[PDB]
Length: 167
Ligand SMILES: [Mg+2]
Image (tube, rainbow, N blue to C red; front, side, top):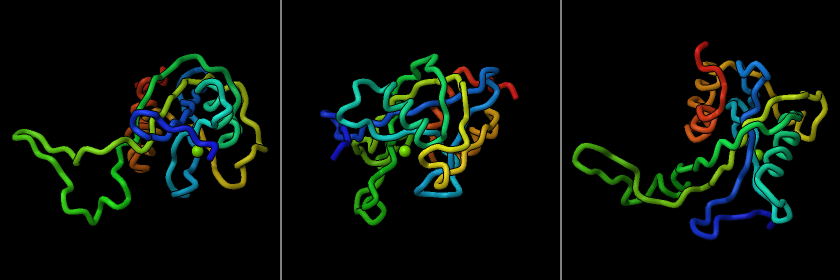
């Protein structure tokens, strides 16, 4: 009941960080709690008392990755467009238009507000440090992790960052 939702779409409002090394060659990823073998980036629900998305983003980056640094860019918004859980056994599923196919119209699950952070410190002890792993990855490696994790929206956030893509 601390959770904030879009007054328009009902999507849950979430903020997180693309945390880059000063040389911009690697990004910090954490293992998912829902899927322990899948590598994602730190993010979490904005809480009712938080005054801005930067606050949520830096709180989640500390709670989930033991990462501290400074926000150096606003990477804007991306949306979790994954269908509902009930969808799989539904009657109508897809919409087709002559030269393309799309999944049937639905509201986003989540609206993500992402910021790029320059890592200033990684600490060995942090709130979720026994419940998650956290590791730096080059662009090529991070990109493959996020496809494997089935999170293209997190890949879109990574691609807006200043991470060096010429590995
Ligand atoms: Mg989270």
